[PDB]
Amino acid sequence: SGFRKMAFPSGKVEGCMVQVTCGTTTLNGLWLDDVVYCPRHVICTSEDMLNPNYEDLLIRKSNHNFLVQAGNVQLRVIGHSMQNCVLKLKVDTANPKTPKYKFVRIQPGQTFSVLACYNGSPSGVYQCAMRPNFTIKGSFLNGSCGSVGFNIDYDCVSFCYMHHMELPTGVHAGTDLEGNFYGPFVDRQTAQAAGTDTTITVNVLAWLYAAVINGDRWFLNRFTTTLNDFNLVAMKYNYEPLTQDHVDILGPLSAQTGIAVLDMCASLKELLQNGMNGRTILGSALLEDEFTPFDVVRQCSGVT
Amino acid sequence: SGFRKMAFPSGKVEGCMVQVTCGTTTLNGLWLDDVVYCPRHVICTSEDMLNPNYEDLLIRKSNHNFLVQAGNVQLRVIGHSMQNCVLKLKVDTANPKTPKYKFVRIQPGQTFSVLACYNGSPSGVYQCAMRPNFTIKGSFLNGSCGSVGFNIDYDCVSFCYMHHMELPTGVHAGTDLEGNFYGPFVDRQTAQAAGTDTTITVNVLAWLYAAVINGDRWFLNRFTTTLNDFNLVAMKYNYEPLTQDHVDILGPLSAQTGIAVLDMCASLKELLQNGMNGRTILGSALLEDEFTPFDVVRQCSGVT
Ligand SMILES: Fc1cccc(CNCc2ccco2)c1
Ligand SMILES: Fc1cccc(CNCc2ccco2)c1
Image 1 (cartoon, rainbow over the protein chains, first blue to last red):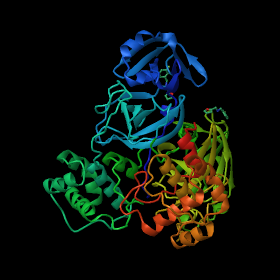
Image 2: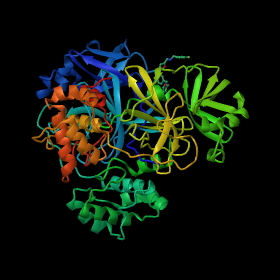
Image 3: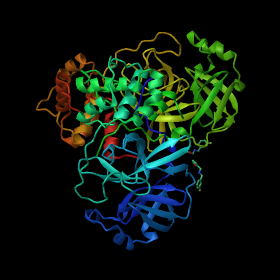
Image 4: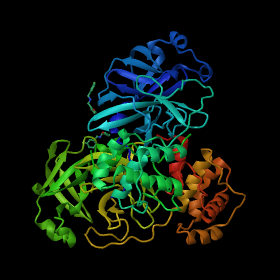
């Protein structure tokens, strides 16, 4: 029993983190096989960042201009290319600690773990979701860029995120490991405003299931609803619409608890209309939306 | 910017986790040098657990009765002793992945990271505090016993906790790595009730500082107070008393933000008397007490 905001163990990712320096700019890189992946803005002076032309800035750079340090030992860069907003530095040594891995582009509402690093050294690990506006609410200081988001399936690290930007509102933007930004963001120090940070409805529902499973039941009501009825209320409350895809995914939690998905939807609806009345669920005073259905099953069944 | 509930990277601890089996009972052990530490109740049948005599149960056990598996390779047990509520199994191989480490007995309100494991395999990592009633609010299923709590200072893992018990109320009890329980708990399946789960006042104050630092300022008021005045209100609200020791420790956050500790105390006092009025601080609807002053400095300054 107990339910916790739980990150994947970070060991497999700690073994991939390096320091990348280009001139006076230092940030984190990900060393997988003989490639080091890092934010392309490593090549910019914070002056460059105001309106950088990366292709033109890159012309000025050679393999030897990129310093890669893994522990306190330098790696030899024998090639570099830009892919979208990341640099791929070919090093002469394949990473001894390279885990099995994939690069995956996740969907808004998907959760992942961040290993926050500075100078290629890990400082901490936390659990995140991709917000529906394709931002994340991270904890990231200067030097944290190139810190990565991941999921683990048994022994295979799926890398989904690389940290690039803090927006003026202090939320975070970054790329998949092919250098494609989540959302409409660009690696430039310019006014960029996020869209509406809606609640991930399917995740709240999963966490309501986690709560029932763990004995927090006070909020279970005598009502059910429909997807259409619920989705009218959702809209009003800046909740994401719920689809039959979300209902399908909640099936196993529905089955384990014997609470039909639409009944839990009606429980949620009343929580939205009534608020918590100073009560808590799993020691939270608001509805938590940073557990997926898969997260709740995993934690509640004890997957390793 | 951003503030996150952040665990230490778990890599150094992942490399210490083994499976310990004694008869039909399997749980996690910690392999440091040539010793495997695990809960002594590894020797019990859930029948034994109702009123176990560990010394008498141990007489029946030899070195060879303890099966230790690290990855999928067996370690040879060449000795065993009981120290308080842990078994120390001497193995013939020192752990290649042994980090620099210490065993430390932490104080209530101290935070640490848990690497939740099953069959000596890590499933997740989360950040905890030792509650003032010497329980923790973990996430722990059957097979999680021997999972450990730790802090890291640069390259040195301080092990402070080993998981033993879930109380009937679903909160968790365990030992330091010398097998001494936190609080008045015993490794026995018997009615054991926790005392009052008070709020860690100094930690709430630290997190109020973290909030000011990150731009959440709405709650800052026009009042100050005294330790005595504040401690009257604290008492009423099941907050731990604040000492000059807590004030000393908050000094650096006070200095960085220019908010005197007693002014922040008066801010807290009003939050207690008024509640949040449906507002949030660092995206929380209640006051967070699972960041220490040292946690807030570390995260806000970016230590690795
Ligand atoms: F040069 C290499 C290139 C790719 C893989 C490897 C071996 N990686 C083993 C491993 C997994 C986790 C920690 O170490 C070495
Ligand atoms: F047999 C041994 C006994 C004690 C220590 C060691 C070496 N430990 C090195 C290390 C640190 C982190 C990962 O590996 C080996």
